[PDB]
Image (cartoon, grey):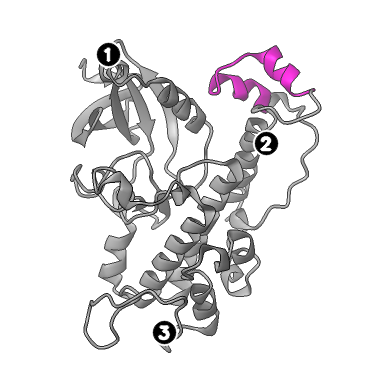
Amino acid sequence: SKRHIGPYIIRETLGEGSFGKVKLATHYKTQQKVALKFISRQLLKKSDMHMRVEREISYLKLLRHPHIIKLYDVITTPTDIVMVIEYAGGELFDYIVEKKRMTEDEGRRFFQQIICAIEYCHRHKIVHRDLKPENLLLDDNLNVKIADFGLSNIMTDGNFLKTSCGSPNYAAPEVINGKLYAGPEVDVWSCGIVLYVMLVGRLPFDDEFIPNLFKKVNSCVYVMPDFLSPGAQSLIRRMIVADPMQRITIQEIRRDPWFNVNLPDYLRPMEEVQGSYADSRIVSKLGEAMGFSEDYIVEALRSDENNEVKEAYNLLHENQVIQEKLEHHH
């Protein structure tokens, strides 16, 4: 290229994603690192599908949660559409095994970040729900950043060929007898697994004597290390339940006493009003990113109910309130 793209001057290519290179760049005046994901317009056309992408991304344009990697912008060049993705150099599991076994105040800190992240999805019907070690990133403040941008282990390892369960590059489509892989209760199962791993250091379902030997997944998990508190066991026991239907939901996880201990304010539950979709501060913004038009937006927001717009309003509003609780606070 020209070495530049928008405010971002290229700096190094970190790995290769199917549709193009993933490059590291820094805002030209600010120095802010950022990850530039390249999508070839050529290759887009070739696959008889560009519409689902073009929109899947203008959609992401408006998710701004503290524990989900942000899409700051989409920049189209004559040859590529490049997604400007938030930068994060660490991987949660790497930290797990270095710390080996964490304290409860630590496991819980991380766990709250993850549970709140996927609740924000479930609530805005997003599918940013792939939760494998590669998707669980960490920034310099040890904050979890869930990443589902088909980035493999590029930002952590440089390894763009890492793949795991649930992906076509990993295994055949039929292996996953699940179109229900989009069930909210799958995210609770995975989250239960991560919690155990963070708190215990090893994985569950292990033969009790032989080290790292997978045994079986019983209907539920009875015995766990005694160093795990009763609050921690009870919660895990309620997440790693075989039958999806007997599994706890994130609504309940969020009312749980254990889970709530030390919950940072910007993460507290919000049982929102709603009303007045009459804020021009966000009305103007609903344009810039979602695209669309003012009056169209202004119109949509008089209706006597839920378009895709009387909720992208509420999404931008939720993002605002939790950005205020983050900074106008200690």
**For the residue carrying disc 1, how many other residues have a C-alpha within 10 Å: few (<14), some (14-19), or many (20+)?**
few
| Quadrant for the C terminus in the image | bottom right
Q: Is residue 264 left or right of residue 216?
A: right
Left/right of residue 296 with respect to residue 31 in the rendered view: right
User: Tag count in the figure?
Assistant: 3
* Prevailing secondary structure of the magenta residues: helix
Q: Residue under label 1, please give it.
A: 79
Q: Amino acid at mark 2?
A: Asn
* In the depicted structure, whether residue 123 falls above or below residue 296: below
- N-terminal of the pair, mark 3 or mark 1, is 1
Q: Measured from the top left, where is residue 70 in percent x and y? A: 44, 38
**Which residue is at 57% across, 41% downward?**
125
Instruction: Report the residue marked by disc 2.
Output: 314
Quadrant, the N terminus: top left
x, y (%) of residue 3?
21, 20
Residue 43 left/right relative to 123: left
Looking at this view, is 209 or 309 the one in front? Answer: 209
At label 3, which amino acid type do we have?
Met
Front residue of 175/112: it is: 175
Quarter of the view holding residue 11: top left
- Secondary structure under badge 2? helix
